[PDB]
Image 1 (cartoon, rainbow over the protein chains, first blue to last red):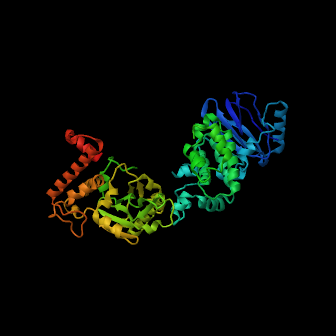
Image 2: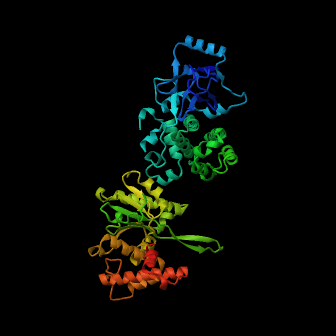
Length: 300
Length: 253
């Protein structure tokens, strides 16, 4: 069970770890998060009490190094850093644990929610979407734009999601205009699955990563990407049975986890109505259609 | 963005543009079958592709053979229209290719955008204008070439005949839209107004009669009267009580 110690908490902040959150007071003896489950990516995230515009976090995997958080009073944020000295780190974590200065990652034994949201999400794929190769963890915030948003500015601070555009030459074969526009199977299966992602696992990993960035940071470009990847599947007449069954599971847990109070900003009426009620896959997403109809019937 | 009364004058500037009307592409007669079900029979159609500045009409005749063994014909018709417009553009020398294509129906936007991806600098636009181009098949010579076609055919016309020798393209378009609006509202009455002086004929190389400037003013007035009379007959409105402002509004409107 891994640990992300904190040097201190000099500013009042709401700290998120995965789907969990807790309030830390200015100069409270908070020194980090212990018992973090090995085997999954994690996200530690921040919203400052004095400025809710400061919404940002770090994707990391404790198998890839020893990470800690230290407040930077110059840049005014909680930064993640890697500690290279294994023995120094182990000694710091042991002292804070002994003085019980750490919150425990509060996982219920029955509860597969985080696995279910991150099943296909890999740290190596995150680092290709979020490019900062000198660090093993990836910084995301609420204002970061996508490569596609920047096409329609700073390329170093962008989310490199795979560009999906239904009215692009990539999406439409010359001579198959109507066919390829009305049935996106060629774009899904040849261009995106075989061509770019290589397999459905990498496609779902990006879809799941986009959703989580949308939910945890309110990142608008991420929300656009999540919807575009759902719509590309739902708008394809020919999709492997295993992909549709898995998509149904992915979306069910995403909709289950979404706070009701954010449904109006994080869910696109057009895409969901189309996917569930008009698309080729309108009858393929049983679990997702049931939770959406019972939780968000107004949207539909 | 959208073509409105925002600026109508953009139609007559020196940027090559075409209107595309797909109304007459997919045309059917609905009939009873022997078992008393209903069936359609397609008839020949046309794409109406018009340069409003020059009067150049690229009439692509849609032969019924196009539909054979196809499903969802009203959807396919939009895509076949877009295919044929994109083929026309590619057939024109670069200096004749339009800068903008205006579709008369918003349903043509995605099909034409998708067929023209190769032409990112050609703007595809809707219009707020209610244009009476559906009435094109009320022009006898255009109806004739469509209904006689035994195969796909493109025929080039000038829909303004020789009017641009005497009038601006703004005025020529205003005359064309008034004629077509009248033909659309009351075809028989419009044809009677156009053809009831045997002394004024249609040249072999023209679509409309050879009216003098004074005769065009009289014809234009009779067309306005027709549209006003039909608006009266339709809505149960005494058109006697209408002012020139009231009348102006109803015809434009």
